[PDB]
Image: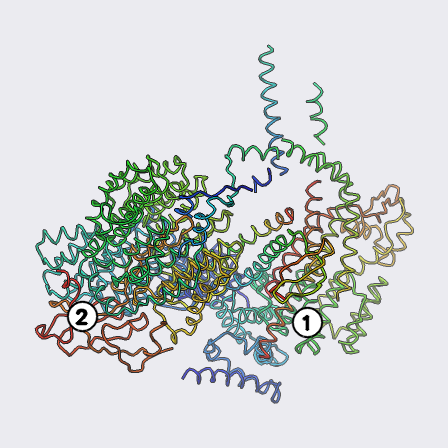
Amino acid sequence: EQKIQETELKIRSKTENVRRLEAQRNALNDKVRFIKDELRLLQEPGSYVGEVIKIVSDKKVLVKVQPEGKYIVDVAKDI
Amino acid sequence: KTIEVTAEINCFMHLLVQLFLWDSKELEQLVEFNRKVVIPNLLCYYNLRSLNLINAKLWFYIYLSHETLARSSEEINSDNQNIILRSTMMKFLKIASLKHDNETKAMLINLILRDFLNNGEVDSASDFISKLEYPHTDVSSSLEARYFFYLSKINAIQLDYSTANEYIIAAIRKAPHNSKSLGFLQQSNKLHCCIQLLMGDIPELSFFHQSNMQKSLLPYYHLTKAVKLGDLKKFTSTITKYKQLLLKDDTYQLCVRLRSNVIKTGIRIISLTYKKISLRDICLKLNLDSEQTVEYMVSRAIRDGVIEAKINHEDGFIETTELLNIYDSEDPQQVFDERIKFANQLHDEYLVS
Amino acid sequence: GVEHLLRIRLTNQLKSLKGLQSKLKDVVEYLDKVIHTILGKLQDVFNLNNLQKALTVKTNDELMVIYISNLVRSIIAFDDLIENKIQNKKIQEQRVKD
Amino acid sequence: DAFRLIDTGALINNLLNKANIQALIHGLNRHYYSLNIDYHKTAKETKMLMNLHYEEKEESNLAATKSMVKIAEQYSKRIEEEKELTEEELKTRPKKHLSETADETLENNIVSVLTA
Amino acid sequence: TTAAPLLALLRENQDSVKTYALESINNVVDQLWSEISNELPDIEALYDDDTFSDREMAALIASKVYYNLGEYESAVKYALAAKDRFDIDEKSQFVETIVSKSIEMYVQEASKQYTKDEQFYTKDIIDPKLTSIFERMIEKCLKASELKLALGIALEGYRLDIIESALKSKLDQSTSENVKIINYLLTLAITTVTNSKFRSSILRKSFDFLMNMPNCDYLTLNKVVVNLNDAGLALQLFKKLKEENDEGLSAQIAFDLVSSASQQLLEILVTELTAQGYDPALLNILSGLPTCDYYNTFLLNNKNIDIGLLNKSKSSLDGKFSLFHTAVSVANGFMHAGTTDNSFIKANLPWLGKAQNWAKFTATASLGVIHKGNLLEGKKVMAPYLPGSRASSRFIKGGSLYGLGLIYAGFGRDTTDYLKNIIVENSGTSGDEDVDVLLHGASLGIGLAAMGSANIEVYEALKEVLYNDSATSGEAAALGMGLCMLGTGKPEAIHDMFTYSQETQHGNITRGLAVGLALINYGRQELADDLITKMLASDESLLRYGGAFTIALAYAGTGNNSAVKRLLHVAVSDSNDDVRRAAVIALGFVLLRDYTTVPRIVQLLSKSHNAHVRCGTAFALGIACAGKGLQSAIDVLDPLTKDPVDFVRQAAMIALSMILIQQTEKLNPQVADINKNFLSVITNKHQEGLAKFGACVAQGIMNAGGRNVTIQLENADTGTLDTKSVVGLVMFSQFWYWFPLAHFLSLSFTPTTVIGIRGSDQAIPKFQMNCYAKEDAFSYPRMKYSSKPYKVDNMTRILPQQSRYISFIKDDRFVPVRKFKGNNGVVVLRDREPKEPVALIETVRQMKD
Amino acid sequence: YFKLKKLEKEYELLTLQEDYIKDEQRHLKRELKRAQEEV
């Protein structure tokens, strides 16, 4: 009868241990993942700056890039 | 049925709080009824949950009036009443758990410990010290302060000044709840003041000005000056005048124990100094303390650790070193070890919150 | 390319022990068969963690200093900790309003 | 990179089905496709790289000794790092740096103690 | 106060002083124990002395003193020793706690003593004083006549003899009470005792104790024979069934045993039936024909299958990877499973003309999924397409044999031999990838047909295909030796297999022998421990992957802590991408019985780094929580479904579907979104090939067997394990080099059915039945507490949730002889008036005789 | 008494889960350091 009560305490205790560890686990886990995304970004040739000369209504745009010559390029669908 | 039994328990508790000084006329006249509500295993009957709707402070107030030979009025001369009550509180401890139900547990050890301090021995004390130590996150701010207050008194008797110094400082911290701006604060304060004097000296009373009455403050100033000047004659007189306070606290022993520190302090003030020291100059200093025992007192000083010096009595001159230079005595090492404890211990609790 | 293919005091002391131990065994063998300076610097020099003893005097002073530096860092961890307690404290508070 | 051209009767027999690659193979007959990069090496190589990468163990003793020599300067800069650090936290009221900044200092002391 | 007065007298040093101080000491020890502690040396000295007269009282005091310190075992020694002044039919709070501690102590000695010798219990050989208390504690609880408290303790203190006696004396036939207690103790011994040697002993005894009563509960009696899996237990049972002979009961029992039991077990059961001469009826049942045919009859009528869904699905994607062609051939098989209709495949043939070699083999093998459930019409259908007959490629002829092996698993007796002749034939031919695909199905089929018995004849045949070293066919043969020898392997077979992994230099043969090695240890438990080490002690990736499946399979059913610790440990500490995924997959098999616990173990791991890990947790839940509809499983699988990493989407979609099979709109609000999602993914082009494979097959799971099946790793009809199903899902769960191997899901479909079976007409009533679960919180998908009165009919879709509240109508023209029992699975009727039908139908075994 | 057995299984599973979390965090601290070296 004493024995059943003791098992109930040790469970209650264990869960709080799980709650604490879980919270920290997440903080570290995020940091690795953050660093991986950052690494994918740190592999790039850069973006060129240009000036929109004029837009064509067929989904080309005429750009004078400052890096290079003058180019016809395909308008983005993100803008 | 169930709801009605919980209600029944709330009503007895409630009744028991009301019939005191707090919320009713005079505690002593009322005591017998207060005792009838405890006694015939209705306290027992309460075990729906743990005692934390009635508290040790309350059981203390009813039982002291019943019996102390000064409120009882030597009503009886036996501790028959307390022996049954202590046993019953002891009987609770066995079925009490420590891991998540130590609300009832600390309170019962507080009541038992208290009775030993009121009248008992310093021998049996050791077991009660070890049993006590249980989380301090389960008990109220008020209850934590009382637990520390009693523990600190017990530690003083063993001459563990340091441990009591920490518990007392923690005890009296903030005031989100009462008995840390009331009469209880003044009792704590007196015991703290005593513990610092025991360590060496208390030389600050800044806090105490505002949290103690004028009647307390005067005796605090008289003691600190006696001890700082080193003058035994002023110290003795301070005990003599505030005899009523030292009796009141129930600890006339303090006077006996502190007096030894004063004569030790006097010998210290004028340090070791020059490489040879003249007898006369030291004799003059020891004459103040006790003047027909110059040689004995100086001998006692060396063995004790008040001073360390080397003596010839076939020349009658004193040789010393004078050290004011603090080379390593395991002192970095000590810092590091302490810090690894400090960071981990603090760290875990803060993290749980 | 090497790295793409692939992706303390004690270990050195154990090696040290084994050489000395081997050296002794050789010296016994060598007397038997037969019937300087390097060995002589390898005994007196180390007799006094051993060497590090004599150095310990100087080490100690700097050793307090670098300890104090770790203590500031512990305080700093406590400070960061307090913010975490508040974050938890806020969430609870919002849940009670709601 | 590794690339090979496509072969018929293999890369359609192996990998609606693949309409795309099916019109591609009846069409061009050969076109580039990328082959995977992997490695294989034995355990013998793997063990006896990591005792080179004797130089490492004996080099490790030498390094500990000369580190304690240079510690006079390395001391002073962490003193500076800390002064910046504390000042930073003030201005905000950053925290992240400070924590990273705290961890690093702990690692360095563990090393300083180990040396001696 | 003080005990210092009392103690002063103890030191005077005579007989009178010892006795007075003792009798004083007993009363207020507890409060004053502190002071008394120092005289505890005198008390113990008086203990084993007798220069005084106080010994048993001295031991008593000492117990009390020790107690108050916090040395419970120390107190326990002396409490015992107090002897005549210590009694356990007298209780105080003090008494309760040291009796409790005395049992713990007794438990400790008993664990150790059982391992050491397994008849420790047949004598006292342990501490007499402890033993005395132990028997008397048992008596106390039992005099008060609550038998669950007494039996709990007797278990715990690891002695069998107390269990026997305790129960025995109180079996008084009431009958209701005897049956219920025994059913509780059976459930207990299985679920909570993995001390395998102890557990078997309790099982064999609890079986004979129930069997000996004049009233039995025959459902419970079947459980225990399946578990201990003995033909010998079967024989004793059946001769008892001869004395009380009823054709209805004896028939029910055979419909139970045929499904659950293993192939070899079934085989000795036909032999013993033949030789006992008792019932030629039952021997036909034991050949499996009746049960499968009855399901066919059910699935043909209650099918809800739509080729418009498969049509929609195919037109939603665009071909550009042969993975899509597999996806719809496979979703079709699953959807149309058991309904004997090939309908989609019949409708659309030009795409078939496109399909690569593997994709052809799969199309052919889809017929096998549909035509499972026929063990006489199974063979017949595939005859125009075999080797030596029509087809159009040899890959098509090769898939004909793969599809035959799918069906005829669980009664492969003929088909193993039949296939063997094809193995020996085609070992010469390896010159063309047309023959490698033929011999590849050939090897799959034979391994599947010969499962659960172990024929060395098949093993030796598949092994010469390895020596000839053919690249596709060696994968099927390797996995095939593992399937064939499952749970019944030679120790020799393990050693020969293990060496050959190392020898083989083709990647596929190496992959297939890894998985091959895991299968062959199924159900071994601790007996597999030697091989686990050996697989992990090989420093090959394939072999370390293979090691993880070996624990899952060996330790399956009821979970085992040691087994979970090792698997979680590999999952955390090994960084190899195959290895971490396999060790998470592996937790789900261990944990099938205790499925509640799997969302907590895998909670963390689902939000943990590396996609292979996240993939592995999807599977874990998918296998473990299949059929139950655990609300906690679904909540964990939601994030993973729209995860960036494509094969993570895929596996979560497969996983969701297995748990939520035959669970509907209204019952669960969430499934509408889910089905929406499955559909949207195929239709968008922005998903990749792997994500749409996950999606297509997922629709295929929900809609499987014309909506009438669930996926489970046991029967409901005995409530005891079903091997086939477990094995099916572990091959199913891997697809990474195993692009045609989807088909192993046919073996994991169990119909969700409650149908009545007339005992002498063998037919299904169509009648109205009563129900209290709310219908119209059950619906027809696509294309909550209850007690309220409601209706359902017969030969309509019985859901898991529904099954619990249904009841046979009792009062038309039949007696239902043992009645319904609150779980799925048929119940044999025996008829009041067979000779007029109520509203029967003809089954399919009466369409083909 | 029967009850305790049920509860002991839940406790045990949980205990391993806790130890396994501790271990995972260790591999992560390690991973962090390695990733800073690579970047």
Name the front one of labels 2 and 1: 2
Percent x, y of residue E73: 44, 56
Contact between marks 2 and 1 (CB within 8 A): the answer is no
Q: Is the image coloured rainbow, by chain, by secondary structure, or in one colour?
A: rainbow
Task: Specify the amino acid type for callout 2.
Answer: Ile
Percent x, y of residue F1: 36, 64
Q: Chain of mark 2?
A: E
Q: Is residue B240 above or below residue E504?
A: below
- Disc 2: CA contacts within 10 A as few (<14), some (14-19) or many (>=20): many
Q: Is residue B27 above or below residue E414?
A: below
Residue at the farthest bottom position = B25
Considering the image in quadrants, where does the C terminus of chain B appear?
Answer: bottom right
Viewer-proximal residue among D66 and E508: E508
Residue that badge 1 annotates: B250
Viewer-proximal residue among E141 and E530: E530
What is the spatial separation of the Cα atoms under label 2 and label 1, in whole angstroms?
95 Å
